[PDB]
Length: 211
Ligand SMILES: Nc1nc2sc(CNC3CCN(C[C@](O)(Cn4cncn4)c4ccc(F)cc4F)CC3)cc2n(-c2ccc3c(c2)N(c2ccccc2)CCO3)c1=O
Ligand SMILES: [Cl-]
Ligand SMILES: [Cl-]
Ligand SMILES: [Cl-]
Ligand SMILES: [Cl-]
Ligand SMILES: [Cl-]
Image 1 (cartoon, helix red, strand yellow):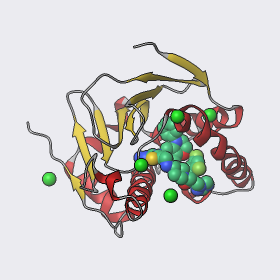
Image 2: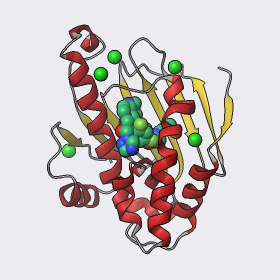
Image 3: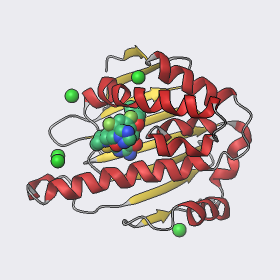
């Protein structure tokens, strides 16, 4: 459909540049942060479903799938959580991330570690430790399916997605940088998940490569 391009908030662009440009070997933290976000989104639909059960008509299973695709050089995290509205994508989430971003940057200047990004609520952006491009497909009840995409550089796009319906939730598609293909391997993904994400209350299925 028609693609709309937007500038990130100045503070968010700056955090993204920092994540992309800083020498920082502990890149695997991205996966814990994205799992955390997926888990939060599942909590939200589960909670809402307690006062409006019809919110689960778009899909009853609450789960997280992690899917490596070597041929495409993608690692995808799929959740069946609440999903994001257009307003979330374009404005609202970035608006709330502003204050967390500022505090995190301040902590970094005062000697904090990039692994504390989650404690500031802006862990999503750690995706850029490993991805050159992130595509996000998302569907909230009573809104339509959207595709968001950013290769950083200060901007992102949003468009109506006409791909396969996901029913409800979010797919985070990480287009990995060339030297980060370890996150496509079985043992590596399992090792990182076990390490950092032991106590998440929804089933996480780590899919295997077919070839
Ligand atoms: N798989 C996921 N599914 C879901 S569904 C949902 C809506 N539901 C909302 C999410 C917001 N919640 C509030 C809060 O959690 C509060 N808070 C503030 N400070 C610490 N906590 C929050 C967290 C981060 C933030 F920027 C703004 C916030 F208001 C309440 C329910 C959000 C969401 N995301 C997600 C999570 C964090 C993100 C982003 C996405 N982004 C993002 C990512 C791609 C494109 C555009 C934008 C960039 C900011 O960060 C997931 O990744
Ligand atoms: Cl923004
Ligand atoms: Cl609510
Ligand atoms: Cl909206
Ligand atoms: Cl809903
Ligand atoms: Cl498996």
